[PDB]
Image (tube, rainbow, N blue to C red):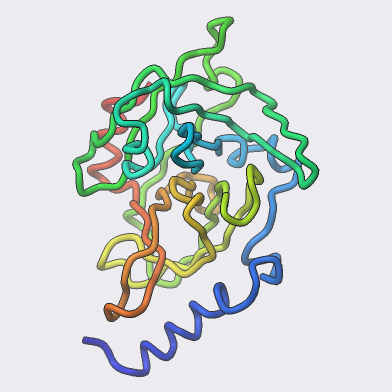
Length: 242
């Protein structure tokens, strides 16, 4: 139970992201990442996780051949690697020209829920290209930080592929942390394709992975939910990363 003043204020904030048309959102809160920035860190660690005829979401290169995304996204492949593809820094302009600067990678193995079924993260291991060159040799993986020092009110950058808005176009979203007692919760503009989007701090460190929207305050309102790279998650990543 929370005061009626909260639901009012929550609705106030929420609405500044979802009350106006996506295209009408202020650039500071949501914007397309241009070509120049796409070639730089941390943007180039972001890729599109494509599951043939199932979904198109986001993933973060955290290892030489490893991509961190959501367990719910990975489930769409039913343990079958041939069904998933990873396209780092893919871009399709409004005129259908698609470019994949580092190529497209095949998956050799899906670790569906290495952190437990109630933690929405999965690891995707990639094959190197046909020359045996790993994606992580072409691009430096994201630096992994920690979510331990984050606090209510913090502002972070969520980077991903908002499919439902624009196909294969990397966008950044400013997010605002809120009641962190109930997991990584935040205000910000996202759509289903942002699932698996990286959340970075001012130091360029990966501190969380976007998951979805969950009920908040009461059963009738929403907030974005993400999985923070906490002590436990960090440990499993150090153990299985590659």
